[PDB]
Image (cartoon, rainbow, N blue to C red):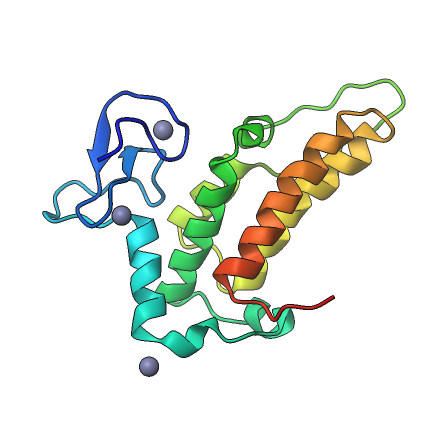
Length: 178
Ligand SMILES: [Zn+2]
Ligand SMILES: [Zn+2]
Ligand SMILES: [Zn+2]
């Protein structure tokens, strides 16, 4: 197994996947690494299994259909994985914890949002459809772009949104377009 966490790239107290060489901090994995379960298979492995059991699941889909899906166990897992892919980028630090807003010439967003809030909401089964999760994720970046205006720091929101959107298209097999 790897000797660093797949998510944060640090060493520490790591749990190792039994079916692939990845390792994780307990609360870096989503969902948090399960108490018992030997063998244990990471989220990467669980997602690969879904694909392998239903090869047709990789054919192109329309976003509007994906968003209306109910949060059954496989869609729950796919959103957990997508969230984890965002945490994998180090620039996610900016969006992880609860933000505050006090900048001359700007007003804070009406509905603040952040990664750890989305993580809690998934853990608590608060989303009934994929749309709920995707709307909160996109709200993170939209709030940031609006608040930072022409400051060059707005670019961090564009960057992490791009990671989100590329992973969304990959995990939910969105039909490729020009
Ligand atoms: Zn970690
Ligand atoms: Zn694995
Ligand atoms: Zn099948």
